[PDB]
Length: 121
Image (cartoon, rainbow, N blue to C red):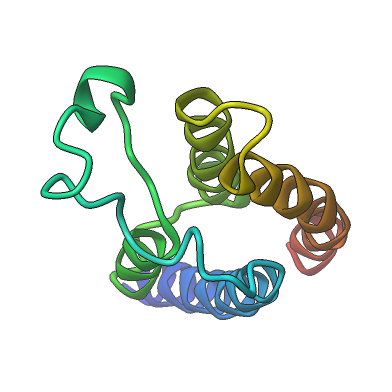
């Protein structure tokens, strides 16, 4: 149908906007601490601590399969990156500190993205 196409164009445009959002969030992680999944070869107990791992490469695969229906689902994944880190790692660690700075800096980007998603519809 023509509606299904219209729908698919909106999703495609949401994916376009979310791709730009993802690039902006990932620039706030210049150390690349959150770039890839925590290695289960290197942290073999990880899944005993963290039940839903997440990282920027994993978000990117979901994004490119247009697997985010709305900004809320995208934010959920970004929040997992931060929140998982802040639980697994202690406060005095470069990892925890990196998460705090990504959260703080990402806030600005996410604030505008929400306005843009509501605005463009």
